[PDB]
Image: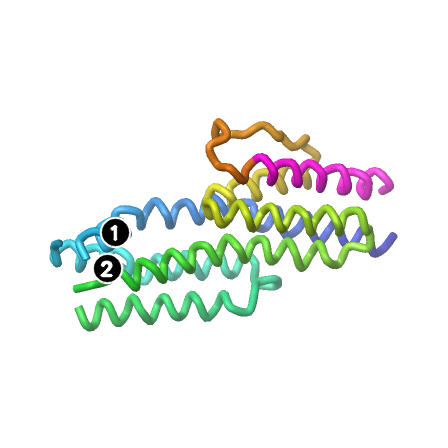
Amino acid sequence: GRLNQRNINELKIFVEKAKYYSIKLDAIYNECTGAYNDIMTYSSDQSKVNQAISIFKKDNKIVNKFKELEKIIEEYKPMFLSKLIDDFAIELDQAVDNDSNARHVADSYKKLRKSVVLAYIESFDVISSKFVDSKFVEASKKFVNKAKEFVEENDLIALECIVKTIGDMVNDREINSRSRYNNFYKKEADFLGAAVELEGAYKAIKQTL
């Protein structure tokens, strides 16, 4: 009983501590989208490449935003996350210092952004693997697999759905298995299904408490 309470509580604390994770990643994306687009395309017009780089580097704000997400999941984060952030920081700094083709900065940004989404799922995975309840463990494994598949299709949309659905679960709100994207993303429906299976298993733990 101590263990099943410790399990629920740990999950609930994490989800609530991370409830802005999707909103915050979206904010990075929105700030960087025009800069990202110009690096990918004008890498032709140099003037624009340098101004796009400036937007990523300015006041180290974007790197600092990734560090903020990293801190939200500090206790669970995957070992790689700190390094990927630093390696991005480094590459951006070389693109600034050695002023023309900046596609590698944009690629490294894309890679980091996907890895931050995957770090949320990694945190959920670690937490869920402490659960004594085997039905919950099985449902968590299926959930993680469907989550990762959805991330491959679209990292930010997948994160938005994972955060929404896990949030709904831990706050006793019924998960909606209806597509919020007119079924545009081929992996949404199965993810939502797995979230509903996870909800049934979680409900069980909860109502025996």
Decide: few, some or many residues near mark 1? Use Cα within 10 Å; few <14, some 14-19, many ≥20: many
The residue that disc 1 covers is: 35
The residue that disc 2 covers is: 53
Q: Main secondary structure of the magenta part?
A: helix
Q: Residue furthest front?
A: 186
Look at label 1 and name its amino acid: Ala
Q: Is residue 203 magenta?
A: yes
SS class of the residue under badge 1?
Answer: helix
- Residue 126 drawn at (x, y percent): 67, 59
Look at label 2 and name its amino acid: Ile
- Residue 162 drawn at (x, y percent): 57, 43
- Residue 150 drawn at (x, y percent): 53, 45
Looking at the rendering, the stretch of residues picked out in magenta corresponds to 189-209
**Picture quarter with the C terminus:** top right
Q: Nearer the viewer, residue 76 or 138?
A: 138
Residue shown at 36% from the left, 66% from the top: 88
